[PDB]
Length: 49
Length: 49
Length: 87
Image (cartoon, rainbow over all chains, first blue to last red; front, side):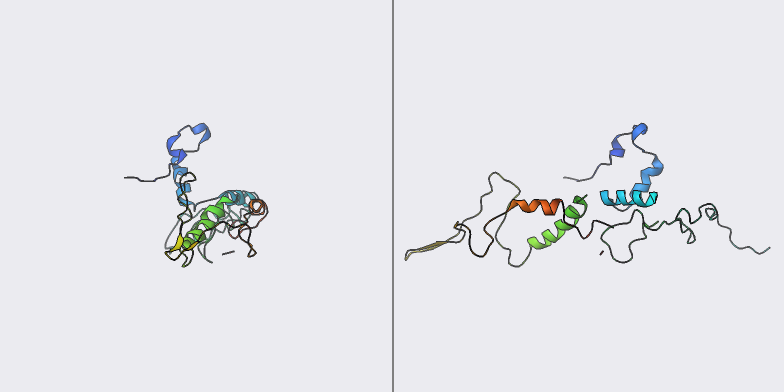
């Protein structure tokens, strides 16, 4: 009887100084399509460009 | 004395396309950013947003 | 940088492949200790004895020998299909 469910560190570390857990961003991430290092990184190139 | 509907956009004049934001449709919408990987021709919009 | 396409994309082609018509037999079971292949001997009362998986040095075909140096070009310099933002 296993529910192999991922635990959002955010949902086990309410220490605001270093883990934006703002309910508001609590959902922007849910909205996002599974990332990656390449994309997280690519946004940076683009957000910055 | 005619107006029909009065939405509350997001002041297009401030978020000029110098912020790469194509705001017409209703919502923001930058082009190349947190794009998903490995998907058909479209699919790059559920989150273009 | 690589697991993004590698675990997510190589993995599937692999699974689909685990089901190919011919790739029969068994290759593993995730356990390094214990798992030992199953042996098959074509035995015959008339004194025949030719096992299927016999060990006999490097053949001419060119498969027998495994070469681990292949890890680097795959790991360091080999572009991917879903890595740099192809379809």
